[PDB]
Amino acid sequence: RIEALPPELFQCRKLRALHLGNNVLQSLPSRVGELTNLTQIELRGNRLECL
Amino acid sequence: EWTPDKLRQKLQTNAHNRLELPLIMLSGLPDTVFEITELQSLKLEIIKNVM
Image 1 (cartoon, chains in turn brown, orange):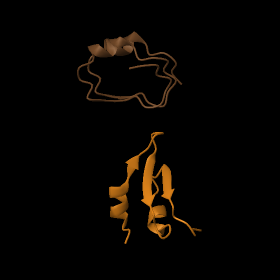
Image 2: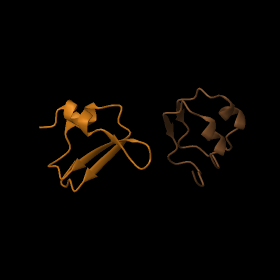
Image 3: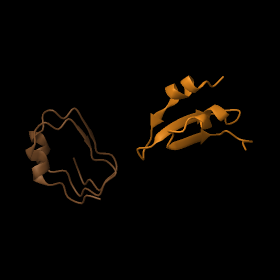
Image 4: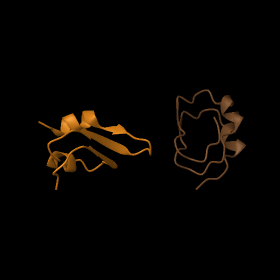
């Protein structure tokens, strides 16, 4: 039960596998563009308005 | 005809992020399907006269 993704999550750059699916994330912040090591991210379901 | 390894091959995901077994136009339901215990979703398509 996570409603909003904190920017401090994206402050780390070493994230590789983000199992964020099936949540109540209102939206994914654009700060995910900082992440480079991210090779897979689970975004199915949720309350994701747009990618 | 349906070894558990064939069911491992058949294993996939669905629209709700569950472990799906797509069974298509089968004569029935094998007990080998129920031998799999990691299964999260069952897909039975036009498999009639099944108990």
